[PDB]
Image (cartoon, rainbow over all chains, first blue to last red):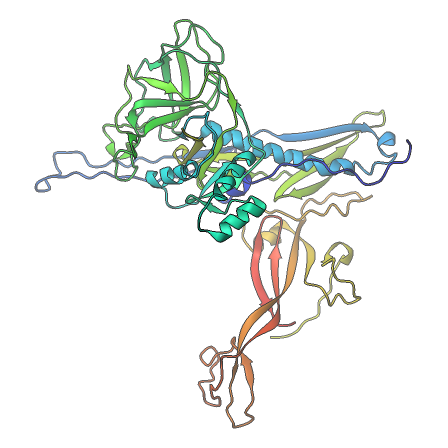
Length: 414
Length: 152
C-alpha cells in the first residue's frame, strides 16, 4: 500500500460548442486602456413612406433621424487558487502539474456556463411549451422557419440540444424510406447530419438549467408602460407592472421566465405585417431579467428583455401589431415550479464574446497558458512564513448582446 | 528569387516534428512546427493592430528561472506536404529541342511566351505531384494564409 503508479487515472470532461458559434470578431481587442470600462456599436436606421395624391408633403411631418447604441461591458474575475505546504506536495507530485491539467478546464467550463445563462436571461424569442421534449423532425425545423419568417438573412443560424434528444432524432432518422447513406450512418454511429431542418443542429452535454419559480393567478397589466423608441433606443429593455398575482410570495418570477402578451402579435420587421403560425397568429413574448417578488395586493414590478415598440410619432420603428395598454391579459409559460434544461436557437449576430489581456503582476513569477484560444495568467507568491505557498489562475470575460429579437429558447410541442 | 540559409535559435523549444518520423533526417515526416518569439510592437508592425495578440502555450521554460519580460508573443510556422493533382502541358516546339513538359502554373498568357517558340501539342495528362505548403498560425487563428513553397 506504498507503491503508486506515476500515471493518473482518466476523468470526466464537458464540451465546448457555444463559445465556438457566438461572434468573437466584432468585440476583440476593443476594450483597451483608452476605451474605458465599456464600448458601444451603432444601430441600423429605418424609414417610413407617406402616400399622397400629388406630393404636397408640406402638410405632414418628414422622418426624424434617431441613432441607437449597443454597449458591451466586462464581467467579474474567474479565479481558481490553491494553497499548500511544499514538502508534502513535493513527495511524489510534480510542481502541482497534476493541478495543471484540470484547472484550465474548470476556468473554460465556467465561461461557457456563464454564456448559457447570459443568452437564456437576455433572449427574447420563445417556441413551444417548456414541458414537452424533442421527439420529431418538425421540432427542429420550426426554429429555422421562425427565424426566416422574422427576416434575418445576414449571419448564420445555430440550434443546441441535449445528448438524449439527439438520439431520439436519430431513431426517427433510422425510420427513413429512401436515403441509403443517412439510414446507414444513423444505424451505425447514431449521428444526425450537419444541416437538420434548414438549421445547423449541435449536441452538447454541458448546458445550464433553470428553475421556473412559483406563480399563480390570472395576471394582467396595470399601467401603460413607455414603449416609445426614444425610451428604449439604447437597451431594448422596459419595465412593466402586473396585478392579479398571489397574495405575497418571494421569488415570484425567476430569471429567464417567458411572459407572453396574448393580444399583441409580432410583425415582419421589414414589411411591417403580422406573423401567422399556420393556424394562429404568433403572440409577443419577453424574458425576465432579474428576480422579482410579490407584495400584498399582488403588485409585481418586473423588468423584461425585448420591447414591443409602438411609437406613434415615429411609426417606422414599430415592432408589434398594437400597443400594450392597461387591462391586457398576459400568461407565463410552463408549470408552477419545475426545473428544466432549455434548448437555445439563435443567429450568429446575437451575442458577442471577448477577452481582456492582463499584464504581468510586478515582481511575481508568472506565465501564460492557452486553452482553446483562451489565455490564462498564473502567478506564484509566498505570502506567509509557514511553508505556505500560493497559486492563482485568472481570466476576465466581456459579454455583449446586440439585438434580443434574434435568439431565445425552444422546446417541443404536442 | 534566391535560396537563403537561416539560423534557428532555441531549437529544443521551437522545432517539433511529426511523431511518426523515425529517421535521422526526418525524411518520412508529413508536418512540422517552427516557433519563435516576437514583441508587441513588431506584432503590430506586421499583420494588424485590430486583433489582440494570442500566443501559443507550451509550459516548457521558466523551469528554475526568474522571468521579468511579459512582452514576448510566441508565433509558429506550420508546414504541410500534400499530394495534389496538377496538369502538365508539353510544349513540343521542334526548334531548340522538342520534348519539354511544364506545369500549369506557367501559361502562355501568364508567362509572355505567346507561342513564339512553343507549340501547344498535348496538355491533358494530369499527374499527382508532391507539394509543400507553409503557414503562420497563433493561438487564435491564421496570421498568414497557407501558400506553397518551391520544393519537395
